[PDB]
Image (tube, helix red, strand yellow):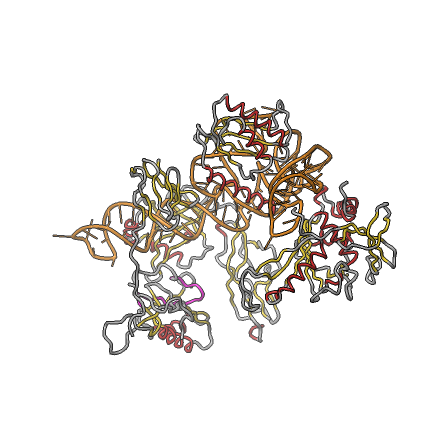
RNA sequence: CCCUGGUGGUUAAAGAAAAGAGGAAACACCUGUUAUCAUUCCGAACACAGAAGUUAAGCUCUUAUUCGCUGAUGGUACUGCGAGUUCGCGGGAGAGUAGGUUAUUGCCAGGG
């Protein structure tokens, strides 16, 4: 059995058809779809505190399911007293089935558990179908336990879509039921 | 891939206590309790107090 | 009509020294190109050119006669030495005498406007206007008197009184050439 | 758009570097290049002193009726060896042609090897 | 207040040693250079310091492709 | 004064300046120009003396454009020294002008007043000059 | 012979963007990760297993030259030489302008 995420089932069985009708696309897979979700977290303070970076990496692992990579400093800078090549950030890429499952978990479970959650700004679009927005308190995810955290942390989420514009991606996200603050 | 650096992903059923909706979602969280999903499949059941359709926003 | 005619004769010298000798003989080397023809190399009388076209602009058009043919040519270029007031080459771009064509033509402002007299502000929005005519009838520059233009008045493009066979070509007919606010 | 274009560009860069690392082929020891489509598998032997294809083979050839598996390319390499021996060429230089020497190409090359062709 | 500077190295005598069309035999030096001002074409080789030398007897020739100069022996 | 605010190198070699002008030899921003009839160097300070003269003569009538900027150091050894050490030190700045450089351009005023003002300017420069109207407009 | 795919030579943008046409074959997108392989995480690339679907994209052809690139003829700068001196002879730009330019070609395979 090729086990399939419920999001993938929902997409393939409805969303393709509604978007074809709604945007008069000539051929079927002109329809937008999702290629990757990038979860990033920038801990510049890790240059003092290694525990911060280790905790962030581990907590990302529990949140998603796959291990993270610690990015390095592209340039040595003094304003943040950064030496080139130091560990400064940590990111995870989600693709395919894991991507769909994570996005489902997020939208239905973790966005609800945010303090004063009143939707998400439906305008954080880079003009090319890529939607990036932040979450300040990782504790919204029930996966991580409260006691073991060493410092409350946030993280940025970027969703990359095959769409050529923002309208297409916003329509796809709305069909997915993404709680945009509107 | 190589296989030694990943937490154990598991299929999990999340149950809303309020609306009763259940979500099938592959969570790394091991739940002590087991539930028979609609599909006759056993899944670790985690009960979550707040979910999608029971938004104070939707 | 003569004052738009220019006498030339062909040259076959083609050298720096040769051109210097010609200009010593008080003529001007010149070339004519356009209409896909072979370039024509010729020479012009400097005194005649000075007398007739002492005020030549990019939009001046004239007639070249080699005794055997007539050509309608724009003064595409003229290599002038300012210190010695010396022309030392002319480029003539030929056009078809009967083909309507466009060209930006500058404006010339005359009169003292009542609005500016009384406290108006000149703002010359447009320094030129796109007109349309056969080559021989293109206006050298289009005149505009501001005297009746009072305060808070802009000049419409149609308001420009135009020579006979010259016609406006601007897409925006209602744009303002000069305003007095 | 740009992503497919850059994938193409990377493939071309690899191909070019491989070519001038292995050098050109001569009638004595010509060059064997391969191409791996989504459906088929192509091989050509080229003499660059002429720009001529001395011999060639691919899974499109109906008579062979091979597939696109390791087994099939093993048999295809066997056929290529027997076709080249009758044209008495035993030394070849192996242009991997922008691919990585692994899997299908590994089996192809080793099959040419077990039957007396110097690659 | 004397001069702060005045210091120059020995000239290294770079440049093309055999002109295009000349006949060379194997091993001749053709160009001495820092960097591939001229690149290598057929039948020549490049030393560890980018010297151009002839792998076989022949006649030097320079070609130009996309603005880069190539040296060959034909 | 008029002087560059930053230089790659503080001192540069005095070339030989010769030939007429093949560029910057046409009236561009104005109505009347002050061409030179020689090839020489115009210091920044003579430049600003001529500029004062023109501007002061013009009672707000129009605008003045300066078509040369000095950017060339002129070094001079200390007063009493010998020929020893080398390349003494920048003293003042020079601009290069060749026969046919427009050098100065004026807008707005009547031609008579412009001619007067610009002879008043020419009285303070080290080169012969000529006042030119556009010679292709009026 | 031609279309397509692959592989050489001839180096002038043989360049990108926008719009239209097709897709039989071929090619590409596309399917699944479970088999060997790869990723400083990620079947994205690559690797392997296959053919449900498509011209949407890549690709091919046709487009205004919209951007770029290339480029006349003259003239000028500059230059060799001269018992002609701002000259006499020889060579001759760059830039600008009239324009032009979205290649061509050798041979391997499939079949029109």
**F20, above or below D68, in the image:** below
Query: Going by the picture, which residue comes out furthest to the top?
Result: D86
Q: Is residue G90 left or right of residue A116?
A: left
Range of residues picked out in magenta = F25-40
Tell me, yes or no, if residue C75 can be seen here. no
Which quadrant: the N terminus of chain F?
bottom left
**Is C28 or A168 nearer to us in this picture?**
A168
Which quadrant: the C terminus of chain F?
bottom left
Q: Is residue F122 left or right of residue F83?
A: right
**G32, above or below C123, in the image:** above
Residue ID at (35%, 44%): E52
Q: Is residue C126 left or right of residue A138?
A: left
**Residue F26 painted magenta:** yes
**Is D113 or F18 nearer to us in this picture?**
D113
Q: Main secondary structure of the magenta part?
A: loop
**C72, above or below A83, in the image:** above
**Is G17 or E59 nearer to us in this picture?**
E59
Tell me, yes or no, if residue E4 can be seen here. yes
**G24, above or below A46, in the image:** above
| Percent x, y of residue C44 | 35, 50
| Percent x, y of residue E37 | 38, 48
| Percent x, y of residue E27 | 32, 40
| Percent x, y of residue D4 | 60, 44
Residue E18: image quadrant is top left
**Residue C104 painted magenta:** no
Residue ID at (32%, 35%): E57
């Amino acid at each position: 059995m090729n086990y399939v995420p419920e999001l993938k089932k929902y997409y393939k069985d409805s969303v393709i058809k509604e978007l074809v009708k709604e945007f008069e696309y000539k051929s079927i897979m002109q329809v937008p779809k999702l290629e990757k979700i990038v979860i990033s977290v920038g801990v510049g303070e890790a240059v003092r505190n290694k525990k911060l970076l280790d905790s962030a990496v581990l907590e990302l692992a529990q949140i998603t399911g796959q291990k993270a990579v610690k990015t390095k400093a592209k340039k040595a800078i003094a304003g943040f007293k950064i030496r080139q090549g130091q560990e400064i950030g940590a990111k995870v890429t989600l693709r395919g089935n894991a991507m769909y499952e994570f996005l489902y978990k997020l939208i239905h479970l973790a966005l609800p558990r945010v303090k004063d959650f009143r939707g998400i700004n439906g305008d954080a679009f880079d003009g090319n179908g890529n939607y990036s927005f932040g979450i300040t308190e990782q504790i919204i995810f029930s996966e991580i336990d409260y006691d073991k955290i060493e410092r409350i942390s946030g993280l940025n989420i970027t969703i990359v879509t095959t769409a050529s514009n923002d309208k297409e991606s916003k329509a796809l996200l709305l069909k997915f039921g993404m709680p945009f603050s509107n | 891939m190589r296989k030694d650096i990943h937490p154990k992903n598991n299929l999990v059923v999340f149950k809303d206590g309020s609306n009763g909706a259940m979500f099938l979602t592959k969570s790394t969280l091991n739940s002590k309790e087991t539930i028979k999903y609609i599909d006759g499949k056993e899944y670790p059941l985690v009960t979550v107090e707040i979910t999608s359709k029971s938004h104070p926003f939707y | 009509e003569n004052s738009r005619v220019l006498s030339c004769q062909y040259r076959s010298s083609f050298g720096s020294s040769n051109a210097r000798r010609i200009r010593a003989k008080s003529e001007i080397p010149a070339v004519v190109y356009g209409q896909g023809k072979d370039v024509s190399h010729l020479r012009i009388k400097s005194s005649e050119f000075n007398k007739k076209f002492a005020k030549f602009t990019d939009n001046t058009v004239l007639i070249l006669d080699d005794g055997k043919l007539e050509r309608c040519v724009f003064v595409k270029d003229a290599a002038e030495n300012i210190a010695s007031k010396l022309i030392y080459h002319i480029d003539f771009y030929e056009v078809d005498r009967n083909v309507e064509l466009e060209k930006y033509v500058p404006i010339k402002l005359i009169g003292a406007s009542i609005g500016v007299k009384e406290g108006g502000i000149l703002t010359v929005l447009k320094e030129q206007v796109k007109v349309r005519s056969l080559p021989l009838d293109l206006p050298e520059f289009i005149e505009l008197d501001l005297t009746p233009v009072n305060k808070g008045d802009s000049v419409l493009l149609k308001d420009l009184v135009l020579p006979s066979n010259v016609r406006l070509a601007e897409n925006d007919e209602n744009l303002e050439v000069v305003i007095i606010k | 758009m740009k992503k497919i274009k850059e994938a193409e560009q990377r493939k071309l860069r690899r191909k070019k570097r491989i070519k001038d690392k292995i050098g050109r082929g001569v009638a004595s020891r010509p060059r064997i290049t391969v191409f791996k489509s989504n459906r088929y598998f192509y091989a050509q032997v080229i003499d660059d002193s002429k720009g001529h294809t001395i011999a060639s083979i691919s899974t499109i050839e109906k008579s062979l009726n091979l597939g696109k598996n390791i087994d099939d390319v093993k048999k295809l390499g066997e056929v290529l060896a027997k076709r080249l021996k009758e044209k008495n060429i035993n030394n070849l230089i192996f242009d991997r042609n922008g691919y990585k020497y692994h899997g299908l190409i590994a089996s192809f090359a080793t099959s040419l090897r077990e039957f007396g062709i110097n690659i | 207040g004397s001069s702060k500077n005045g210091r120059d190295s020995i000239s290294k005598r770079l440049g093309v040693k055999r002109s295009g069309g000349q006949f060379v035999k194997a091993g001749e030096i053709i160009v001495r250079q820092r960097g591939t001002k001229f690149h290598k074409g057929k039948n020549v080789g490049l030393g560890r310091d980018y010297t151009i030398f002839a792998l076989s007897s022949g006649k030097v020739e320079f070609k130009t492709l996309k603005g880069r100069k190539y040296v060959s022996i034909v | 004064m008029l002087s560059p605010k930053k230089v790659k190198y503080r001192k540069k070699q005095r070339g030989r300046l010769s030939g007429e002008a093949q560029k910057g030899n046409k009236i561009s921003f104005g109505e009347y120009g002050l061409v030179s009839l020689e090839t020489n160097f115009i210091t920044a300070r003579q430049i600003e003396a001529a500029r004062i003269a023109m501007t002061r003569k013009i009672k707000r009538g129009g605008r003045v454009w300066i078509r040369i900027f000095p950017d060339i150091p002129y070094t001079k050894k200390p007063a009493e020294t010998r020929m020893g050490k080398g390349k003494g030190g920048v003293d003042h700045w020079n601009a290069p002008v060749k026969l046919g450089t427009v050098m100065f351009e004026m807008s707005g005023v009547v031609e008579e007043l412009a001619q007067e003002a610009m002879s008043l300017a020419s009285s303070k420069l080290p080169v012969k000059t000529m006042f030119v109207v556009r010679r292709d407009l009026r």
